[PDB]
Length: 52
Length: 46
Image (cartoon, rainbow over all chains, first blue to last red; front, side, top):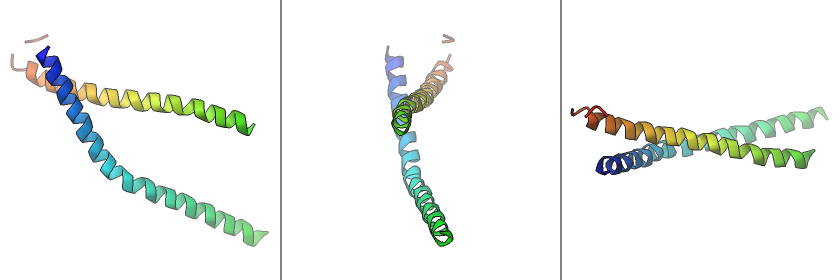
């Protein structure tokens, strides 16, 4: 029972730690991708505008 | 068509989260398994 409890605690901590590392790294990356998407969308529209 | 698409897109995110859940649960199970295996490897085969 104690082993299972310690294991659950250990796993719980591991998940919390691993997630925090990923999150801190991830947050900066999503913004860059979205910015590029919007920029490409605008560029395409501009191109479609000059053609018309 | 647009409404059937938004309804299908809603139905798709559920499976997308269901996969995200399985991936995390696996990560914890492995993490816990490693700690247990290391402990058990003191002797205690089960």
